[PDB]
Structures are given as structure tokens and as C-alpha cells.
Image (cartoon, rainbow, N blue to C red; front, top):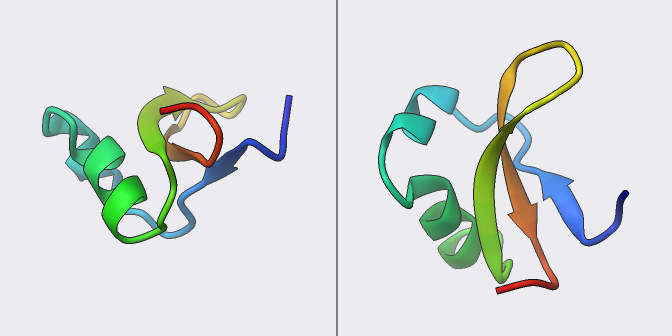
Length: 54
């Protein structure tokens, strides 16, 4: 379900504990439109940036 949603590579995932932090870093640093932390198929938390949805 790709191309809109990209993984923030090398993101320190402790920061997913901070409210809105992945969102914030995705917008300001990756110049994406939003971001949220999700678990991947290896059951690891990831910050995922979204360059389409706000």
C-alpha cells in the first residue's frame, strides 16, 4: 500500500512515545504532510511519513 507512506529511515523509535512527534518530524524534517508510528511485519515500531494525507 505504498508510495504515499514512506518509513523514516534511521528514526529513533523511542520518540514514538512523544505525542505528535513522528508527525512533527515527518513534516518539518522530511517535508511530508503527516506522520504516525506503526508496527511493521517484524513487530518493530516505525515512524511512517505520509506525503499525501495531512
